[PDB]
Amino acid sequence: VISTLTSLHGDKVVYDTIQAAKLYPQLSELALKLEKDQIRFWIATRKDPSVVFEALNLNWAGISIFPKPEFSAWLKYVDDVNARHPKEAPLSIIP
Amino acid sequence: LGIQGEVENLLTDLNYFNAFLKEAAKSRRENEVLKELVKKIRKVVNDAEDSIDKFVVEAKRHDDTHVARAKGVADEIKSIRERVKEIRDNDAYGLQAITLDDEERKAPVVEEDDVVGFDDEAKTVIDRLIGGSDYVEVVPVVGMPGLGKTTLAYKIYKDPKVEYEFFTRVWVYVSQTFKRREIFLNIISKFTRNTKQYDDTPEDDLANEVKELLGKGGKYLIVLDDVWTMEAWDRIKIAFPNNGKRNRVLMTTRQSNVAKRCNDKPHDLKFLTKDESWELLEKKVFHKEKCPPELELPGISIAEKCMGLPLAIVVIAGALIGKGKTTREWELVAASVGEHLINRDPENCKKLVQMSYDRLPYDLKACFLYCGAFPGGSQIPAKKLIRLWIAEGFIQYQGPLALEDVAEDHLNDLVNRNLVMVTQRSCSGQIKTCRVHDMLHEFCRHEAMMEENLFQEIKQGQERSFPGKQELATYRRLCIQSLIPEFLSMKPSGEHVRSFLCVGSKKIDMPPNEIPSIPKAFPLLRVLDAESIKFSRFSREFFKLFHLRYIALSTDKIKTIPADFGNLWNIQTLIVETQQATLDIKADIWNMTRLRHVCTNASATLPSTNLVNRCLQTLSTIAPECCTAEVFTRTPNLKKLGVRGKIDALLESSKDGSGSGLFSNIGKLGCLEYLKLVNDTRLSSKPLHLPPAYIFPQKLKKLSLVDTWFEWKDMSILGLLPELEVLKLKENAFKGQSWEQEDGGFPRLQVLWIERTDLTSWKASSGNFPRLKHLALISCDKLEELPAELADVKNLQLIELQSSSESAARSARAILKRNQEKEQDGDKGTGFKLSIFPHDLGL
Ligand SMILES: Nc1ncnc2c1ncn2[C@@H]1O[C@H](COP(=O)(O)OP(=O)(O)OP(=O)(O)O)[C@@H](O)[C@H]1O
């Protein structure tokens, strides 16, 4: 709730930390809810799709991008911000 | 400090570089510029890691010449940071090139004729294809690369028995990469030639069409050549009909995990014998003609060095043909058989091995190549190998599993992929010793020397000498089989050496003046595998290895480890194969958080200890007087003790009202799984007693008692252990003339080992060994006869006797006769064998 524990001076390292905490049974529920809260930050400020693309680490894949579930969530992200955009200017994954 | 910031920004850069290297290793890079770019980035990644390690250790030293050392560290971190920015500025296009990476179906070609030594193997698999259930059954042929799996599969595929039995025979070349659609189209093209009508049919509808074609063709056999994954098998098997017509699938593969998941008992292919290797090599080199007598002597040696692998024989045969028919030239090939396999013929041997190697996860590749550091043809202790991977840093795992459990899964993964061969498996099923085949061993050497630079062999060859300081400035790790004292004599300077692996099999008594050479030449020494080297004394340089993780040494004169050892906070494994009976660890090793093993060979008198050693797992030998309550408080996750010394103090109870001895502390460990006891008292005549089972460890699995002289009466208490599986008794571990067992006991016992027993008679009941598999009676000359209740064990597999008496031999024959009668009554045999010599006595 406090902005100190939400900005965290970065997003990619936080995302990797959340995934790392997910393998522990005592941290599975905490990491899962924190993962959703990271999407909350992604929607609140409407960061560029380049940052989220790097945060999901889709930058190393050839023909294998589409089968990757990270690509599906990357598509769901742009759809969500296209339902919460402050102005009607389109946001696209293509650039 | 600003230095702390500099290391932080450097760390983020290596986070990108390591991620770049991991994704760069996902496939082979053939472009020479990309190869050098990967080598440059890997070199700066390693060198930066060597410098951050200097920073973090020197920071630890500073917490407890410091200005000069800090200045040198900051100067270094400045240089690698400049070098990293140099790569990011000048090589910026290159880093994108590997990131932006993305054909012909090379079906293997095999001997249609002159298949040497596969007659018995073909009939074994063919008869296995005939039998089985009416449903779909898989018969996977599994083995190491180039073993002859496709050759045997094609031998069966064209065998007259198979061609008569199976009306439909299909060969499908599955591989690492394949199109699920093209396979069903290929199978359809066997029956109907009209391919235009299936241009838009969906894949699953094509599989439905394949189902109709195979089903009408009666009983069918399908050779799924080189299936690499279970996911591929599930994708393809949807088109194989289960008509109940005894149709089979013959699935050659390099994977044992895939083989086992398709059939519970996969068929492992054999190696050619020494006679068959020469017969094949002679056939390949000479076209239907015998070898000249002058070339027979070197040719046989070459075939022996191929280690029975048909791929190596075929490759070396091509070299021999080019090398003429001269004794001198055939002698040169024999002296360099391994070179002619990997280096001179990369298309045949190097490329085939690369298919399995490049498919490994990035962590497994460093583990597999590390097996090539040990001498070719040697056998590597599995326990030693596991601790080497973890101490070096190849096991990077952040789950709740212990590291050795993960590494054991990695080693079993290599064995499953048939990159490693197991020589000995314990009765519990774990791996004991493993070896790498000679072809894969040359691949491990070449890959980890020239491409990856994981380790370097040091030897005094004809064209090679001990490396100079120009070569040592590049070497990451060193492995050495012989001539160690002279290499340490010339005073090398291995600044970047992280490991010193004395893989020699012969004990070397190094002179005392070369002892400080190892720690002074390699200040960054993480792993010191000096098991073969004998050290008579220590030095202050030996305890300056603050980056040390692994330390193994053999001593005869070193009776006590000095307290200076406690400065090495990063050590995990301690090994001391001391020949002395006593050894005192003066170091306060309890504060080393990542301490995992203490494999002492004598009674270790550990010093007196809010902190928990969550990682410590093993203690090979400990003093009974050191079994304090505080010791076991710090080791809750531990999984093995060993207690050598005067066991009288362990069992003696004081008269002050306290009836609980030090064994009560042993039984309070909630995660113990192995216990070993050795007793030193021999002048006394007292036979000893065993404490009740309600103070025994709850989860104990394995036991080993030596020379304790327990009475035979009190092991009915040992039968109250619910999870006991392994029990070993050696050097007259029990005393008494008579052995009698009470009802029940040993609910899960699997193996019982006895050596030099004191008993003369043994009586048992049927309920004593419900799940016994192996019984060993070595040097039991006092045995009169065995009880007949041992024949009631349905799970029994093996009983072995050595140096038994004549009456004991008669009881062994009687038990064998009863076991044979029961097996002939309808219960299929489990593979019993018995050692009897001579066989004509007592028949
Ligand atoms: N029994 C044999 N007699 C003669 N040559 C053999 C024999 N077995 C295999 N070979 C030869 O060894 C080479 C490799 O054998 P094969 O093609 O059967 O490999 P494999 O075990 O299927 O391996 P991979 O996993 O790489 O496909 C071939 O050139 C083949 O001719």
Image (cartoon, rainbow, N blue to C red):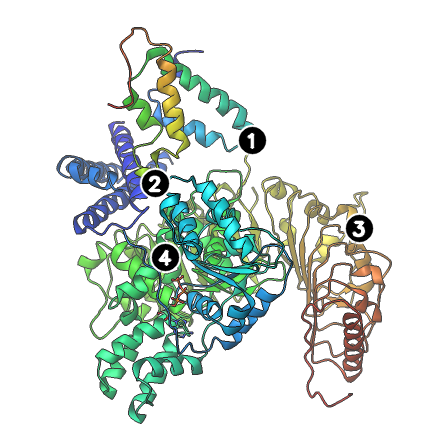
Query: Which quarter of the rendering shows the N terminus of chain A?
Result: top left
Looking at the image, in which quadrant does ligand 1 appear? bottom left
Q: Quadrant of residue B810?
A: bottom right
Determine which of the numbered discs, if any, sits on residue B57 in the image: 2
Q: Are marks 4 and 2 in contact (CB under 8 Å)?
A: no
| Same-chain check, marks 4 and 1 | no
Q: Residue at x 41, y 74 (%)?
A: B307
Task: Look at label 1 and name its amino acid.
Answer: Pro
The picture places residue B375, in percent across and down from the top left corner, at 38, 68
Foreground: disc 3 or disc 1 = 1
Query: Closer to the camera, B525 or B340?
Result: B340
Sequence order check, earlier mark of 4 and 2: 2
Q: Is residue B800 left or right of residue B783?
A: left
Q: Is residue B321 above or below residue B660?
A: below
Q: Which residue is mark 4?
A: B369
Q: Are marks 4 and 3 in contact (CB under 8 Å)?
A: no
Determine which of the numbered discs, if any, sits on residue B805 in the image: none
Query: Which quarter of the rendering shows the C terminus of chain A?
Result: top left
